[PDB]
Length: 185
Ligand SMILES: O=C(Cc1ccc(O)cc1)Nc1ncc(-c2ccc(O)cc2)nc1Cc1ccccc1
Ligand SMILES: [Cl-]
Ligand code: NA
Image 1 (cartoon, rainbow, N blue to C red):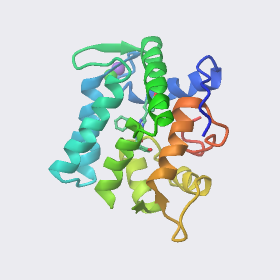
Image 2: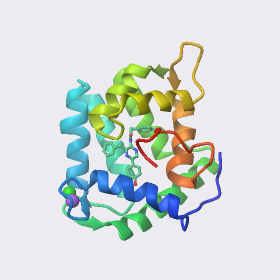
Image 3: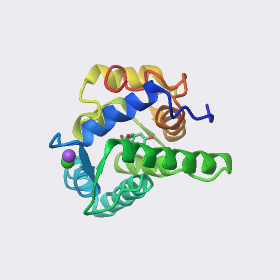
Image 4: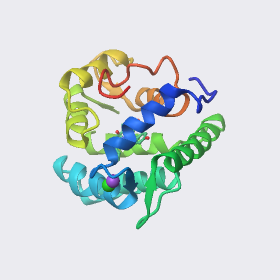
């Protein structure tokens, strides 16, 4: 995977501004850990019918990821501060990768996989995509699967999902471009 960072790249900034606007529910230019974790647990995990343990595992992953960006409960954050937080998460994750230590994004994927499953199906991904709202388009979910290296059953394994997302969120890896079809730039 690309390990070199590209944090000044306008396309990398744009990718995060897209995600930030997506989590900015009321469109006030701020996001909060409170609304995000509520979305993870009270909404996504509820509709997926995750077990209480599966919900909690998913919840602690979401918390760790956004706390990695400097976020905490009861505090609003604007995009530039979030972005610098995300640069700090990104380097922490890449150092973990470089040490053969599990990343937060790997752990979150394990939590997602646990709800469904060592692989997930196109229909299962489509469910997360639509329910989380990251990728409501069936065709974009289908594009994710066309993009990724799948097993002989056409299913997605956790290591492939991990390396794609490490490249997509952290390093603007050209191999990761197109991961969400048109759903996320
Ligand atoms: O989309 C997921 C689920 C997932 C997918 C692949 C993977 O390897 C691991 C996990 N997680 C995710 N992973 C990363 C981001 C994300 C990335 C960049 C950014 O600036 C903001 C959010 N968003 C999300 C969606 C989300 C869900 C619940 C609450 C908030 C957000
Ligand atoms: Cl909000
Ligand atoms: Na907001």
